[PDB]
Image: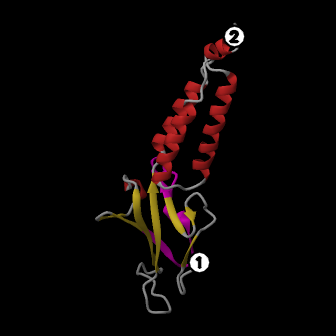
Amino acid sequence: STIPGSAATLNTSITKNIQNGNAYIDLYDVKLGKIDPLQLIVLEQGFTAKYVFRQGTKYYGDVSQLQSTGRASLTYNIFGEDGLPHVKTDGQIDIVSVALTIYDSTTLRDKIEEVRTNANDPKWTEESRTEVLTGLDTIKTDIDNNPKTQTDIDSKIVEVNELEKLLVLKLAAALEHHHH
């Protein structure tokens, strides 16, 4: 919840990015400039924070530099008004470390739009179109609102491919409706 003596606390109300006290960032959102890591914490008056990501063998000071998915860390270094690190009551430097999952819904989102476009072709029965769009809407709502791992993203791509196979041609339906 809040590290004893720390001037910062994780903003758990930002449920797209914070779950179970862990952070998640979707590179899709990053490329749209939608993610400001500073908005994920609440700071006491008189203190500032600078974030630093560690991923692989590199530190990154700008969220826009994240380019690979996987596990990483997100740290907020906390500074007093003099620009120096805050030292807490307990004699330790004030830093807030958060486990980070980086994922990318970009290909899933493209896939979803491709199936949507396909499904909207009037050659498909309305009943199959509707079932397919319903499944796509469920997935899209989920990724819009809820953080995922890349494994989960990849599994949803498979679900989307499978949904697309539910489309039925009006031609096929008209010939099933025939009687000899």
Q: How many numbered marks does the figure carry?
A: 2
Count residues near mark 1 (Cα–Cα under 10 Å), then give few for <14, some for 14-19, many for 20+: few
- Residue 67, labelled with which disc? none
Judging from the image, what secondary structure is the residue with disc 2 in? Answer: loop
Report the span colored magenta: 25-51
**From this viewpoint, is residue 39 visible?**
yes
The residue that label 1 is drawn on is 1
Dot 2 amino acid type: His
Where is residue 33? Give x, y as percent: 48, 50
Give the residue displayed 58% in from the left and 30% down from the top: 116
Which dot, 1 or 2, sits closer to the camera?
Answer: 2
> Could you tell whether 33 is left or right of 125 in the image?
left
Is 6 part of what is drawn in magenta?
Answer: no
Where is residue 155? Give x, y as percent: 49, 47
**Which color scheme did the rendering employ for the protein?**
secondary structure
The residue that label 2 is drawn on is 178
> Could you tell whether 161 is left or right of 166 in the image?
left
Where is residue 19? Give x, y as percent: 57, 64
Where is residue 21? Give x, y as percent: 55, 70
